[PDB]
Amino acid sequence: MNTVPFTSAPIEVTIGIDQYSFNVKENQPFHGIKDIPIGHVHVIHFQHADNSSMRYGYWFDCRMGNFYIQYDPKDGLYKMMEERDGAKFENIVHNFKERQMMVSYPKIDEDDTWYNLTEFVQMDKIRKIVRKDENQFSYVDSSMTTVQENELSDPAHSLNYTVINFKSREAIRPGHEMEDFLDKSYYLNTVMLQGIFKNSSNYFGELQFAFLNAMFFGNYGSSLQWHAMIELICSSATVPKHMLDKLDEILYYQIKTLPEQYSDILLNERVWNICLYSSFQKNSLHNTEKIMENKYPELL
Amino acid sequence: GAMNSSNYAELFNNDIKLFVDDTNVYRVTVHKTFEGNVATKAINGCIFTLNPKTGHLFLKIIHTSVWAGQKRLSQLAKWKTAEEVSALVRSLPKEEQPKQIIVTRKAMLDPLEVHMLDFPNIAIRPTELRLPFSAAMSIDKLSDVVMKATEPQMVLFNIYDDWLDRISSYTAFSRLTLLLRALKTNEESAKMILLSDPTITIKSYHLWPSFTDEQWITIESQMRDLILTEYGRKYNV
Image (cartoon, rainbow over the protein chains, first blue to last red):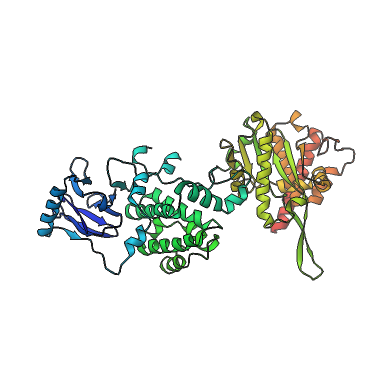
């Protein structure tokens, strides 16, 4: 069980850790989060009480180093940092724990939600989508644009999601225009799975990462990426049975976790109606169709 | 974006453009079977591809053999249209390729955009205009070459005959749209108006009769009267 200590909490802020969140008061003696489950990526996220604009946060994996949060009064944000001195770090964490100035990661033993949302998400893949190679953790916020959004303007601060475009030479083989546009199987299976992602695990990892960035930061480009990757599978007549079964589980947990009040801005009516009711896979997503019909029948 | 009443003069500028109408590509007769079920029989169709500035019409004849053994023909008809338009653009020298293609039906946008990915600088546009190009098969000489075709064939016409020697392309397009609107509303009455005086003939190399400027004004008046009457009938007003 790993720990992300905080130097201090000088400004009033809502702190998220994965799907959980806590209010911290200005100068509250808060010194971090303990009992963080090893084996998963995690995200620690922030919304200042004085500017409910710019949700921002850090993807990390405690197996890759010792990370802490320290407020920077110049840049006006909570920053993740790596402590290279193991003994200094263990000594800091031990003191804060002894003085019980840390919140405990509040996982219910029965509850597989975070595993289910991050099953295929790997820090090494996150670091290729979010480029800042001198850090082992990745910063994301509400306003960061995607490589695809930028094509249609600072490349250093971009989300490098795999570009998916249904009306592109990449998507459409010369002489198979109608076939490839109406059945995207060659785009899914040959271009994306065999060609770019190498396997379904990497494809699902990016899909799950895009969802989480859409949900935790209201990142619009991430929401577009999540929908495009769902639509590419649902619009393919030929998908491996194991991928469809796994996709139904992935989407079920995503729809289960979404705040009920954000369905209007985080769910694309056209994509979901097409995927559940018109697409080749309209009868392959039983769990997802049942939770969507019971939780968001308005959207449909 | 969309071509409308507001940006109408754009049709007659010096940027090459084509209208594409797909409404006569897939044509059927509906009939009863021996068992009393209903079946369709395809007949020859055409793509109507028109330069509104020059009058150049690229009439691609769609022979019934292209539907043999195919499913979802009304959907295929849109893609076959887009394939043939794309093939036509590729066949033209670069300096003759359109800068814009305007489709008369919004269902052609995606098929044509996908077939034209190799031409990112050619704009594919819808129109809010309700153009009467469906009535092209009321022009006897166009109808005749479509129905006689025994194989796929491209036939080139000038839909304005020699009018551009005497009038602008705005006026020629207005005349064409009024003739086609009339032919669409009441074909029998429109053709009676066009042929009633046997002294005015259609030249072998023309589609329409050889009216003087004065006779065109009378013809154009008779067509407008035909259209308003028919409207009062349709709508009891």
